[PDB]
Image (cartoon, helix red, strand yellow):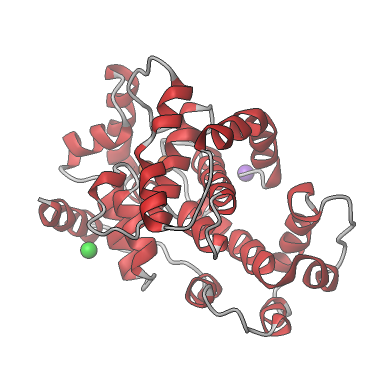
């Protein structure tokens, strides 16, 4: 009954007069992720007129995670030092942050952003460790995964207020509370939204299926599997808000997570040890959380 939930999701957006938008640069970048031979200076040139976006990009570029110890002070430095993929990634991040800032609701702006940035970054780490060829695509799917909660929070806040208090009082997940109160969730709303924005279906499906990887109706589902894992990981390691049923052992859950099999079926040649990946994440999650929390203050 996804169409029932998808129909309800579209009706839920109908009642909003002015719907959120994303910059053309976000859609442009989203569209070009698979083209290895784009000219870096063309990408760089997109920032030229935008002093605010430019300064944001130089700031993220200079962060340890992007730069290491090398000082990035101009955009010219960022171009030379980041290269095409990390530059697309940094620009995407610095432009999409306006979506997460431009509103208020019952959940704090910073809650949704920090969780989304965490998911993006962890999902990318997984992409890298499992040999996935275009990890920026996983990053972008990750950062957008909960764009539906952003919508409900900012645009149907009066209503989301009730989701929050049902969650806080009966200790169910946001997705469960949404299902009960609205008959649809941020998965379906986020899908409807991303479809309205003309985002590729690899992103749309990640938004739709990220709370149950086992629902994806096709075999090559690496990105979704990566972001679903990253979301559950973040939620279980203090980088989230959506809630989770009680777990006997988190490490064991993460080690046995269904995404690992989905990634292996999608990437026939990839050899990885999910035990060591979970261990690595756990060893760096305090640092990851610090970096996330510090980048932009929303
Ligand atoms: Cl739809
Ligand atoms: Fe979610
Ligand atoms: Fe999430
Ligand atoms: K503020």
Quarter-of-image position of residue 59: bottom right
In depth, the one of 155 and 141 nearer the eye is: 141
Residue 6 in which image quadrant: bottom left
The quarter of the rendering in which ligand 1 is drawn is: bottom left
Please determine whether, in this image, residue 194 is positioned above or below residue 281.
below
Q: 284 or 11: which is nearer to us?
A: 284
Location of residue 10 in the rendering, given as x and y in whole percent from the top left corner? 20, 59
The answer to whether residue 249 of the structure is visible from this angle is yes
Q: Taking 54 as reference, is 140 left or right? A: left
Above or below: residue 242 compared with residue 70: above
Query: In the rendering, at what x and y percent does residue 188 appear?
Result: 25, 53
Is residue 65 placed above or below 273 in the rendered structure? Answer: below
Tell me if 286 is positioned left or right of 31 in this view: right
Look at the image and tell me whether residue 146 can be seen.
no
Residue 58 relative to residue 277: left or right: right
Q: Quadrant of the C terminus?
A: top right
x 32%, y 42%: residue: 211
Q: Position of residue 142 (x, y in %)?
A: 48, 52
**Closer to the camera, 129 or 208?**
129
Farthest residue in the top direction?
248
């Amino acid at each position: 009954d996804v169409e029932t939930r998808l129909t309800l999701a579209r009706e839920f957006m109908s009642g909003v007069d002015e719907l959120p938008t994303v910059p053309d640069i976000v859609l442009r970048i989203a569209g070009k992720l698979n083209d290895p031979d784009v000219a870096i200076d063309e990408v760089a040139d997109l920032l030229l007129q935008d002093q605010v976006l430019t300064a944001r990009v130089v700031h993220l570029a200079n962060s340890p995670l992007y730069s290491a110890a090398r000082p990035i002070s101009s955009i010219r430095d960022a171009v030379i030092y980041l290269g095409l993929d990390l530059l697309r990634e940094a620009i995407f991040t610095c432009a999409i942050v306006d979506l997460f800032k431009t509103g208020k609701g019952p959940l704090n702006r910073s809650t949704l952003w920090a969780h989304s940035l965490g998911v993006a970054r962890i999902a990318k780490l997984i992409a890298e460790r499992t040999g996935f060829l275009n990890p920026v695509n996983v990053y972008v799917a990750g950062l957008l995964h909960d764009v539906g909660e952003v919508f409900i929070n900012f645009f149907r806040g009066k209503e989301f207020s009730q989701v929050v208090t049902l969650v806080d009082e009966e200790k169910i997940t946001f997705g469960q509370a949404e299902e009960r109160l609205f008959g649809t969730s941020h998965c379906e709303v986020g899908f409807a939204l991303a479809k309205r924005w003309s985002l590729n279906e690899f992103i749309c499906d990640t938004i739709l299926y990220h709370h149950d990887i086992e629902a994806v109706p096709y075999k090559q589902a690496a990105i979704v599997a990566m972001v679903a894992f990253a979301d559950e990981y973040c939620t279980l390691r203090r980088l989230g808000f959506e809630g989770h049923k009680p777990v006997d052992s988190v490490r064991t859950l993460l080690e046995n997570h269904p995404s690992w099999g989905v990634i292996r079926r999608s990437l026939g040649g990839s050899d990885f040890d999910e035990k060591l990946i979970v261990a690595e994440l756990d060893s760096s999650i305090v640092e990851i959380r610090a970096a996330v929390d510090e980048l932009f203050l929303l």
